[PDB]
Amino acid sequence: YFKLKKLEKEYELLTLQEDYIKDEQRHLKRELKRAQEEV
Amino acid sequence: DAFRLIDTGALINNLEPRQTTSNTGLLNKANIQALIHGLNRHYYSLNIDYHKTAKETKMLMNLHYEEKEESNLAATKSMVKIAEQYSKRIEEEKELTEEELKTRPKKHLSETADETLENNIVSVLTA
Amino acid sequence: TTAAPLLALLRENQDSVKTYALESINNVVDQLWSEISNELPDIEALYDDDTFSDREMAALIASKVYYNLGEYESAVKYALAAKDRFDIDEKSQFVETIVSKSIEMYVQEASKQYTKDEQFYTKDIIDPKLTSIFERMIEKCLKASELKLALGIALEGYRLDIIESALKSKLDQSTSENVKIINYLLTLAITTVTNSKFRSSILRKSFDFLMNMPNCDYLTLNKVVVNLNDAGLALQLFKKLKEENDEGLSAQIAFDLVSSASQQLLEILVTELTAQGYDPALLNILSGLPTCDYYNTFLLNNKNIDIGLLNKSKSSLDGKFSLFHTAVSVANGFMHAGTTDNSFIKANLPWLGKAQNWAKFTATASLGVIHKGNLLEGKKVMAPYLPGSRASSRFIKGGSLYGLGLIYAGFGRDTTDYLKNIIVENSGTSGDEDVDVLLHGASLGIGLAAMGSANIEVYEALKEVLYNDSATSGEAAALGMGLCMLGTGKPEAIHDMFTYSQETQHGNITRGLAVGLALINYGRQELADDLITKMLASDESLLRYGGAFTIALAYAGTGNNSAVKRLLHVAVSDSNDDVRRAAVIALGFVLLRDYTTVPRIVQLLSKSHNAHVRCGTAFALGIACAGKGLQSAIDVLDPLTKDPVDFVRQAAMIALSMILIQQTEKLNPQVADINKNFLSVITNKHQEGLAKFGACVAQGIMNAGGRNVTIQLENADTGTLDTKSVVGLVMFSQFWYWFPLAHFLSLSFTPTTVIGIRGSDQAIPKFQMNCYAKEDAFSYPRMKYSSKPYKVDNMTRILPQQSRYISFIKDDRFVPVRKFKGNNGVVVLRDREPKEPVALIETVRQMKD
């Protein structure tokens, strides 16, 4: 029972890293506009 | 960059004014960088900060139904030119295709497809 | 083979025909369920017929329509009308699913209805068909002699009837196994149960289970009391132990509740137990007065560090271009913490002359960390620095009051009336340069002395200071009210500090109120969402900055998946480099539950852009994993060390220093190259100024307290977090607004050693202890695997890895009680037949009185 609930928390840890990258990839395009135009 | 005189009162002979030292370093160019704490009288490094309120945020947002008329105004000129606009896009993609076949490039071909996408979906929005 | 012949006989009216047609479907199922879906509405129509008595067998097959179709939502609903026709022990493919599917339906109807009432399982709110099946699986697990599956399924169902009946019936007496089962459900309630209301009910029931048996583990008895934070069950433990008082019984729980209990919990045990009688020798121990005196001798004679380490680093830079003078006073306090060694200040006289009044602020306050643990000499040694004596500047008095609250923190109730009355007298009359500096230090003194203790007069005394619109005296006045709101606090101050923050045009006052909001909610978890939303909705960069600290403190320890998503959205939204940095620092406090998954999140943010954010990701490994350390976390901090950015290397040497505390060869081979880099930055003069701050701090962290203490936010005893340790580290990772926030790190110092105390003489005996800590396996540095045993007396340095195998010898006539729990802390022993004293360790108490 203890090891069964450990797998449920691992699915949330994979979701935290998955939802952040999907949001980061769209924000990287905003930093590219501040980069190539400024330099 | 800014430079401030010294009214003291926090300094007198030797003290440590200007709380919250953070952000960037000295930088600048040459002369005033060599001496900072040695001679603080007429020169020393500073930082620049800007404070805006809630009303000042939308003040610069006015760049983007007045502008709606200009959206359909550009569509009027392209309405008669819809045959001439796509004529130059298709003939350009044909010439870029032969250059890719004779390479045996994709950068110049992708730039033409991007302008075609903006001339299609936006033209559909007129209906 | 089609289902048409068997299903066509139900269109007529007969008693025998309707029986034979239904029973034939139960025999052949997997073949005929294809055509039953078309006849499904005709079969379910017979359930409402009162003259049809086969509905028990009909509902069993009707549930198999969606069960064979692949939809389990409707399969469990129609299977509840079978009554006795529903098999249990058959253990077939249909039984192992619908029963398990009913468990999921039992949980969905539980947590949603648990908010309204917890008794729904008794009443008709929940379908009794699901409850009856839920109880049959409980008795099935009892026959298998497994308490994990029987008691674990009731935790997610929110039912107190099975947990109390099943766990108590299995108690036998011996009791060592029953306590472990109780310890499991307390840890299982952290993972499975996401609600704090259900935990409060388990903590109360698990307490009375061990109170009926005379032999029980006393560490678990306090485990349910500290997490509940209630005085009802706390006083009940001392009632049974009144006549049961023993050397290693009543005195064993006194030292464990010093840092476990809050400020309000310690004041109740002293006042309430006074009327019923109490041991006069055990009085000051509950408050913690003598507790700090036990380690004054331990950190003195056992200190192997050399004083010349700070002299060589300080002599490198002096006079013109004065920076380290603020940082040297910080590094001086760590190494001399608890040893009461002032010789460094009296060593080089020109260092006091070159130190300015602003440098004397951290120089006079450095005595609070050095003399921390001695409450008698706190005001005696600092008397010339304390107010009332003529000095050369007001910063000397203001700098002394800041360090005055370090030693007296939590005990400042005696000095509270003295400090806050000066602020009231200086509130109406102000504007002078000497008045604002005097109150600026007084606000820092009243805050740290009253830190942790809720006081109404302290909150009201600092309210009128903000109305005068003074940023010098208003900045310290905002942080003083937040230190008293730790833990629960007053919810009325949430809306007051939030409203007055937007009406103030001062930057330091608005920032102080935003940071104070995070200190109001401590351990609230989802209960702090009301303040989190209001702070993130505002456009102020200061209010949005403190929003990440609220998530860090409330979700500290046990976290939640929804709290991490909020910290990740703020870093990608706000353009402030400081607010984005506070988001990655707050990720360390939510991961305190498991230190293994910490580097997995940090490694993704180490290679990203925004070097200001990369500076905060370095402390992410200096918060959670700093108490233990990992080899995988070292590679994450490698690119931050080679980063040419100045302030990134500042955060790298600090994080690498806390991980390498008490590390030597044959343990972490990388400690040699990293420790030499701390002195290389000081030696190299080509480095910039911003990169040399972390060099003098890192050398004082590893040597802090003579390597007799470590930096840890908590330890495992009752399964709780320290109030002053978690809040103190939030500032330790922040150098931007005010650099020497590391003075708050002194409250988080946890000495690591095993000190036995014999209750006969109320002193520390001397005897050997069999352990695996021999230097051939684990040792300590000087200026995994275990084979051979080891023996050493008390009052010796014991690493946190060495404290797990410590065992007391029973041939010396010393009866252990706590034995080894796998961590540090005082273990009070017992005595069987007292005759004559064996040995005694002479402490510094004999040299004074």
Image: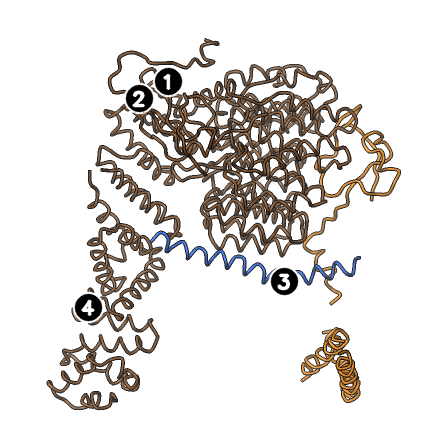
Chain colours: A blue, B orange, C brown
Please name whichever residue, C683 or C697, is drawn nearer the observer in this view of the structure: C683
Label 2 sits on a secondary structure element that is loop
* Contact between labelled residues 3 and 2, with CB atoms less than 8 Å apart: no
Across and down, in percent, residue C110 comes to: 32, 59
Residue C814 numbered mark, or none? 2
As shown in the figure, which amino acid type bears the numbered disc 4? Asp
Mark 3 crowd level (few <14, some 14–19, many ≥20, 10 Å Cα): few
Across and down, in percent, residue C516 comes to: 56, 40
Distance Cα–Cα, label 4 vs label 2: 59 Å
Residue C87 numbered mark, or none? 4
Q: Which residue is mark 1?
A: C765
Label 4 sits on a secondary structure element that is loop
Across and down, in percent, residue C233 comes to: 31, 36
Q: Is residue B116 left or right of residue C19?
A: right
Disc number lying in front (4 or 2): 2
Q: Which residue is mark 3?
A: A25
